[PDB]
Image (cartoon, rainbow over all chains, first blue to last red; front, top):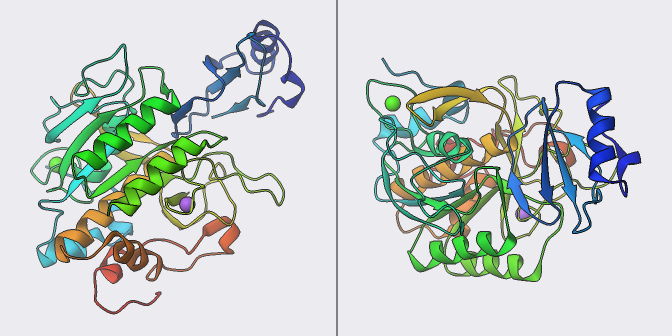
Length: 63
Length: 281
Ligand SMILES: [Ca+2]
Ligand code: NA
Protein backbone atom coordinates (compact mmCIF):
# COMPACT_ATOMS: atom_id res chain seq x y z
CA UNK A 1 0.00 0.00 0.00
CA UNK A 2 1.65 3.24 -1.22
CA UNK A 3 -1.29 5.56 -2.07
CA UNK A 4 -4.48 6.52 -0.15
CA UNK A 5 -7.05 8.02 -2.60
CA UNK A 6 -9.86 7.14 -0.12
CA UNK A 7 -8.41 9.81 2.25
CA UNK A 8 -9.03 12.82 0.00
CA UNK A 9 -11.63 15.06 1.65
CA UNK A 10 -11.12 13.52 5.11
CA UNK A 11 -9.65 15.38 8.11
CA UNK A 12 -5.88 15.46 8.50
CA UNK A 13 -6.40 13.64 11.85
CA UNK A 14 -8.19 10.66 10.32
CA UNK A 15 -5.63 10.54 7.49
CA UNK A 16 -2.73 10.32 9.98
CA UNK A 17 -4.51 7.56 11.92
CA UNK A 18 -5.20 5.49 8.79
CA UNK A 19 -1.76 5.89 7.30
CA UNK A 20 -0.07 4.87 10.57
CA UNK A 21 -2.20 1.67 10.69
CA UNK A 22 -0.99 0.72 7.24
CA UNK A 23 2.57 2.01 7.66
CA UNK A 24 3.41 2.40 11.37
CA UNK A 25 6.92 3.72 10.81
CA UNK A 26 5.71 6.46 8.37
CA UNK A 27 7.28 9.88 8.72
CA UNK A 28 4.27 12.11 8.16
CA UNK A 29 4.62 15.76 7.31
CA UNK A 30 1.65 18.07 6.90
CA UNK A 31 2.04 20.81 4.28
CA UNK A 32 -0.30 23.37 2.70
CA UNK A 33 -1.77 22.37 -0.63
CA UNK A 34 -0.32 24.44 -3.49
CA UNK A 35 3.25 24.61 -2.17
CA UNK A 36 6.27 23.51 -4.12
CA UNK A 37 8.44 20.83 -2.48
CA UNK A 38 11.77 18.98 -2.80
CA UNK A 39 11.87 16.09 -5.27
CA UNK A 40 13.93 13.50 -3.39
CA UNK A 41 12.23 10.12 -2.90
CA UNK A 42 11.95 8.94 0.71
CA UNK A 43 10.38 5.51 1.09
CA UNK A 44 9.53 6.19 4.77
CA UNK A 45 7.81 9.54 4.12
CA UNK A 46 4.18 10.47 3.52
CA UNK A 47 3.46 14.12 2.85
CA UNK A 48 -0.17 15.17 3.57
CA UNK A 49 -1.30 18.22 1.60
CA UNK A 50 -4.12 20.04 3.33
CA UNK A 51 -6.54 22.77 2.36
CA UNK A 52 -7.13 25.81 4.62
CA UNK A 53 -9.80 23.79 6.56
CA UNK A 54 -7.20 21.07 7.44
CA UNK A 55 -8.84 18.49 5.17
CA UNK A 56 -6.80 16.34 2.75
CA UNK A 57 -6.67 18.04 -0.66
CA UNK A 58 -4.53 15.63 -2.71
CA UNK A 59 -4.05 11.84 -2.77
CA UNK A 60 -1.43 10.94 -0.11
CA UNK A 61 1.42 8.81 -1.47
CA UNK A 62 4.70 7.44 -0.20
CA UNK A 63 7.80 9.37 -1.22
CA UNK B 1 41.11 10.35 -1.42
CA UNK B 2 38.27 11.60 -3.57
CA UNK B 3 35.61 9.30 -5.07
CA UNK B 4 33.77 9.86 -8.35
CA UNK B 5 30.08 8.96 -7.88
CA UNK B 6 28.91 6.57 -10.62
CA UNK B 7 26.42 9.07 -12.05
CA UNK B 8 29.19 11.58 -12.84
CA UNK B 9 30.97 8.87 -14.89
CA UNK B 10 27.71 7.62 -16.40
CA UNK B 11 26.94 10.94 -18.13
CA UNK B 12 30.60 11.07 -19.38
CA UNK B 13 31.61 14.16 -17.39
CA UNK B 14 35.23 12.87 -16.93
CA UNK B 15 35.69 13.21 -20.74
CA UNK B 16 35.09 16.96 -20.43
CA UNK B 17 37.35 17.17 -17.36
CA UNK B 18 40.18 15.47 -19.30
CA UNK B 19 39.77 18.02 -22.16
CA UNK B 20 40.28 20.71 -19.47
CA UNK B 21 36.67 21.83 -19.01
CA UNK B 22 35.12 21.86 -15.54
CA UNK B 23 32.50 24.66 -15.61
CA UNK B 24 34.90 27.55 -14.82
CA UNK B 25 33.24 30.99 -14.78
CA UNK B 26 29.76 29.57 -15.33
CA UNK B 27 27.19 30.80 -12.78
CA UNK B 28 24.75 28.09 -11.57
CA UNK B 29 21.88 28.94 -9.18
CA UNK B 30 20.70 26.02 -7.04
CA UNK B 31 17.12 27.16 -6.28
CA UNK B 32 16.47 25.00 -3.28
CA UNK B 33 16.68 24.75 0.56
CA UNK B 34 20.00 26.59 0.81
CA UNK B 35 23.57 25.26 0.62
CA UNK B 36 25.84 24.58 3.61
CA UNK B 37 28.74 26.90 2.65
CA UNK B 38 30.95 25.50 5.47
CA UNK B 39 31.24 22.11 3.71
CA UNK B 40 34.93 21.64 2.71
CA UNK B 41 33.91 19.92 -0.57
CA UNK B 42 31.83 22.95 -1.75
CA UNK B 43 32.63 26.53 -2.66
CA UNK B 44 29.60 28.81 -2.62
CA UNK B 45 30.16 32.05 -4.58
CA UNK B 46 27.03 33.91 -3.42
CA UNK B 47 23.27 33.75 -3.05
CA UNK B 48 20.15 35.07 -1.38
CA UNK B 49 17.21 33.77 0.65
CA UNK B 50 13.51 34.28 -0.32
CA UNK B 51 12.29 32.36 2.77
CA UNK B 52 10.79 34.93 5.21
CA UNK B 53 11.69 33.01 8.40
CA UNK B 54 15.08 31.64 7.22
CA UNK B 55 17.17 34.60 6.06
CA UNK B 56 20.56 32.86 5.65
CA UNK B 57 20.91 31.10 2.23
CA UNK B 58 24.20 29.53 3.45
CA UNK B 59 22.48 27.53 6.14
CA UNK B 60 20.71 24.45 4.90
CA UNK B 61 18.33 23.18 7.57
CA UNK B 62 16.88 20.46 5.33
CA UNK B 63 19.97 18.88 3.64
CA UNK B 64 18.45 18.60 0.17
CA UNK B 65 19.94 21.78 -1.40
CA UNK B 66 23.43 20.77 -0.17
CA UNK B 67 23.13 17.31 -1.75
CA UNK B 68 21.88 18.80 -5.07
CA UNK B 69 24.70 21.36 -4.99
CA UNK B 70 27.35 18.63 -4.61
CA UNK B 71 26.12 16.84 -7.69
CA UNK B 72 26.42 20.13 -9.68
CA UNK B 73 29.75 21.27 -8.33
CA UNK B 74 31.47 19.33 -5.52
CA UNK B 75 35.13 20.43 -5.62
CA UNK B 76 37.93 18.57 -7.42
CA UNK B 77 40.41 17.80 -4.64
CA UNK B 78 41.51 14.90 -2.44
CA UNK B 79 38.27 14.61 -0.40
CA UNK B 80 34.66 13.52 -0.64
CA UNK B 81 32.99 13.39 -4.03
CA UNK B 82 33.59 15.07 -7.38
CA UNK B 83 30.89 17.24 -8.97
CA UNK B 84 29.82 17.27 -12.60
CA UNK B 85 31.15 20.86 -13.01
CA UNK B 86 33.61 21.18 -10.09
CA UNK B 87 34.79 24.71 -11.09
CA UNK B 88 31.33 26.23 -11.50
CA UNK B 89 30.38 29.40 -9.62
CA UNK B 90 27.73 28.03 -7.26
CA UNK B 91 24.88 30.23 -5.95
CA UNK B 92 22.61 29.29 -3.05
CA UNK B 93 19.13 30.66 -3.83
CA UNK B 94 17.07 29.56 -0.85
CA UNK B 95 13.33 29.30 -1.60
CA UNK B 96 12.44 26.23 0.51
CA UNK B 97 12.43 26.02 4.29
CA UNK B 98 13.62 23.30 6.67
CA UNK B 99 10.50 21.24 5.90
CA UNK B 100 11.33 21.12 2.19
CA UNK B 101 8.42 23.33 1.07
CA UNK B 102 7.97 26.81 -0.29
CA UNK B 103 5.27 29.20 -1.46
CA UNK B 104 5.02 29.82 -5.24
CA UNK B 105 5.98 33.48 -4.67
CA UNK B 106 9.26 32.44 -2.92
CA UNK B 107 10.23 30.26 -5.93
CA UNK B 108 9.35 33.09 -8.33
CA UNK B 109 11.40 35.57 -6.27
CA UNK B 110 14.41 33.20 -6.48
CA UNK B 111 14.02 32.84 -10.27
CA UNK B 112 13.85 36.66 -10.52
CA UNK B 113 17.00 37.02 -8.35
CA UNK B 114 18.77 34.54 -10.66
CA UNK B 115 17.84 36.58 -13.77
CA UNK B 116 18.88 39.89 -12.12
CA UNK B 117 22.23 38.39 -11.05
CA UNK B 118 23.09 37.03 -14.53
CA UNK B 119 22.99 33.33 -13.75
CA UNK B 120 23.88 31.10 -16.72
CA UNK B 121 22.03 28.02 -15.39
CA UNK B 122 19.17 27.43 -12.94
CA UNK B 123 18.60 24.07 -11.28
CA UNK B 124 15.18 23.46 -9.67
CA UNK B 125 15.07 20.08 -7.87
CA UNK B 126 11.54 20.90 -6.82
CA UNK B 127 7.96 20.70 -8.05
CA UNK B 128 4.22 20.70 -7.43
CA UNK B 129 1.24 19.18 -9.26
CA UNK B 130 -0.28 22.57 -10.29
CA UNK B 131 1.17 25.45 -12.24
CA UNK B 132 0.44 29.15 -12.06
CA UNK B 133 0.58 31.89 -14.69
CA UNK B 134 3.12 33.76 -12.53
CA UNK B 135 5.34 30.63 -12.27
CA UNK B 136 5.19 30.09 -16.02
CA UNK B 137 6.04 33.76 -16.64
CA UNK B 138 9.11 33.59 -14.35
CA UNK B 139 10.60 30.51 -16.09
CA UNK B 140 9.74 31.84 -19.56
CA UNK B 141 11.38 35.17 -18.61
CA UNK B 142 14.56 33.41 -17.46
CA UNK B 143 14.77 31.47 -20.72
CA UNK B 144 14.01 34.57 -22.80
CA UNK B 145 16.92 36.25 -20.94
CA UNK B 146 19.38 33.50 -21.89
CA UNK B 147 19.33 31.20 -18.80
CA UNK B 148 19.40 27.38 -19.15
CA UNK B 149 16.56 26.24 -16.84
CA UNK B 150 16.58 22.59 -15.60
CA UNK B 151 14.08 20.93 -13.23
CA UNK B 152 13.23 17.55 -11.71
CA UNK B 153 10.37 15.83 -13.62
CA UNK B 154 8.73 14.70 -10.34
CA UNK B 155 8.50 11.41 -8.41
CA UNK B 156 4.85 10.56 -9.20
CA UNK B 157 5.54 7.32 -11.07
CA UNK B 158 2.91 6.14 -13.58
CA UNK B 159 -0.84 6.77 -13.79
CA UNK B 160 -1.97 4.86 -16.88
CA UNK B 161 -1.69 7.07 -19.94
CA UNK B 162 -1.74 10.36 -17.97
CA UNK B 163 1.30 12.61 -17.70
CA UNK B 164 2.65 12.83 -14.15
CA UNK B 165 5.33 15.46 -14.80
CA UNK B 166 4.92 18.31 -12.29
CA UNK B 167 5.62 22.06 -12.48
CA UNK B 168 7.87 23.83 -13.36
CA UNK B 169 9.28 20.81 -15.21
CA UNK B 170 6.05 20.54 -17.23
CA UNK B 171 6.47 23.96 -18.91
CA UNK B 172 7.96 23.77 -22.45
CA UNK B 173 10.64 26.36 -21.56
CA UNK B 174 12.07 24.14 -18.77
CA UNK B 175 14.15 20.99 -19.31
CA UNK B 176 12.35 18.25 -17.31
CA UNK B 177 14.66 15.47 -16.10
CA UNK B 178 13.69 11.91 -15.15
CA UNK B 179 15.69 9.38 -13.16
CA UNK B 180 17.51 6.24 -14.20
CA UNK B 181 19.75 3.85 -12.24
CA UNK B 182 23.28 2.60 -13.07
CA UNK B 183 21.86 0.09 -15.62
CA UNK B 184 19.90 2.86 -17.39
CA UNK B 185 16.58 1.55 -16.10
CA UNK B 186 13.94 4.13 -15.24
CA UNK B 187 13.44 4.42 -11.44
CA UNK B 188 9.89 3.24 -10.55
CA UNK B 189 9.10 6.62 -8.90
CA UNK B 190 10.27 8.71 -11.93
CA UNK B 191 7.42 10.85 -13.44
CA UNK B 192 6.31 10.11 -17.00
CA UNK B 193 4.62 11.93 -19.88
CA UNK B 194 5.37 13.65 -23.19
CA UNK B 195 6.93 16.58 -21.19
CA UNK B 196 9.76 14.31 -20.01
CA UNK B 197 12.80 15.59 -21.85
CA UNK B 198 15.97 13.70 -20.79
CA UNK B 199 17.10 11.26 -18.09
CA UNK B 200 20.08 11.24 -15.71
CA UNK B 201 21.22 9.11 -12.74
CA UNK B 202 18.84 9.47 -9.79
CA UNK B 203 19.25 6.23 -7.77
CA UNK B 204 21.71 5.93 -4.81
CA UNK B 205 23.51 9.15 -5.71
CA UNK B 206 26.36 9.99 -3.31
CA UNK B 207 26.81 13.70 -2.60
CA UNK B 208 27.57 16.36 0.10
CA UNK B 209 25.33 16.73 3.17
CA UNK B 210 25.42 19.45 5.84
CA UNK B 211 27.97 19.34 8.68
CA UNK B 212 30.73 17.87 6.52
CA UNK B 213 28.90 14.65 5.71
CA UNK B 214 28.14 12.61 2.55
CA UNK B 215 25.32 10.27 1.66
CA UNK B 216 23.27 8.48 -1.00
CA UNK B 217 19.92 10.04 -1.97
CA UNK B 218 17.27 8.99 -4.53
CA UNK B 219 15.00 11.17 -6.62
CA UNK B 220 14.44 13.15 -9.79
CA UNK B 221 15.97 15.85 -7.52
CA UNK B 222 19.29 13.95 -7.90
CA UNK B 223 18.92 13.58 -11.68
CA UNK B 224 18.26 17.32 -12.43
CA UNK B 225 21.71 18.59 -11.15
CA UNK B 226 23.55 16.10 -13.41
CA UNK B 227 21.91 17.97 -16.33
CA UNK B 228 22.46 21.44 -14.78
CA UNK B 229 26.13 20.52 -14.21
CA UNK B 230 26.36 19.17 -17.80
CA UNK B 231 25.04 22.53 -19.09
CA UNK B 232 27.83 24.27 -17.12
CA UNK B 233 30.49 21.95 -18.64
CA UNK B 234 29.16 22.68 -22.17
CA UNK B 235 29.18 26.46 -21.56
CA UNK B 236 32.76 26.29 -20.19
CA UNK B 237 33.88 24.66 -23.48
CA UNK B 238 31.60 26.88 -25.66
CA UNK B 239 31.12 30.15 -23.72
CA UNK B 240 29.22 31.84 -26.52
CA UNK B 241 26.65 29.09 -27.04
CA UNK B 242 23.12 30.25 -26.21
CA UNK B 243 20.79 28.47 -23.84
CA UNK B 244 18.92 27.32 -27.00
CA UNK B 245 22.11 25.68 -28.23
CA UNK B 246 23.07 24.13 -24.87
CA UNK B 247 19.57 22.63 -24.56
CA UNK B 248 19.61 21.22 -28.07
CA UNK B 249 23.13 19.87 -27.64
CA UNK B 250 21.92 17.83 -24.64
CA UNK B 251 18.70 16.69 -26.30
CA UNK B 252 20.35 15.80 -29.63
CA UNK B 253 23.10 13.60 -28.16
CA UNK B 254 21.34 11.44 -25.58
CA UNK B 255 21.75 7.66 -25.60
CA UNK B 256 18.19 6.64 -26.49
CA UNK B 257 16.60 4.25 -23.95
CA UNK B 258 12.96 3.13 -24.11
CA UNK B 259 9.74 4.77 -25.25
CA UNK B 260 9.84 8.57 -24.84
CA UNK B 261 6.78 8.56 -22.57
CA UNK B 262 8.94 6.78 -19.92
CA UNK B 263 12.49 7.86 -20.91
CA UNK B 264 12.14 11.10 -22.92
CA UNK B 265 15.10 11.30 -25.31
CA UNK B 266 17.26 9.01 -23.14
CA UNK B 267 20.36 9.40 -20.97
CA UNK B 268 22.39 12.59 -21.39
CA UNK B 269 25.94 12.27 -22.70
CA UNK B 270 27.88 15.49 -22.04
CA UNK B 271 30.93 14.31 -24.06
CA UNK B 272 28.80 14.06 -27.23
CA UNK B 273 26.84 17.25 -26.36
CA UNK B 274 30.03 19.33 -26.12
CA UNK B 275 31.24 18.33 -29.63
CA UNK B 276 30.33 20.60 -32.53
CA UNK B 277 28.47 17.93 -34.43
CA UNK B 278 25.67 16.18 -32.60
CA UNK B 279 24.09 12.76 -32.89
CA UNK B 280 22.70 10.07 -30.56
CA UNK B 281 24.82 7.17 -29.37
CA1 LIG C 1 36.08 16.49 -3.82
NA1 NA D 1 9.52 21.12 -19.83
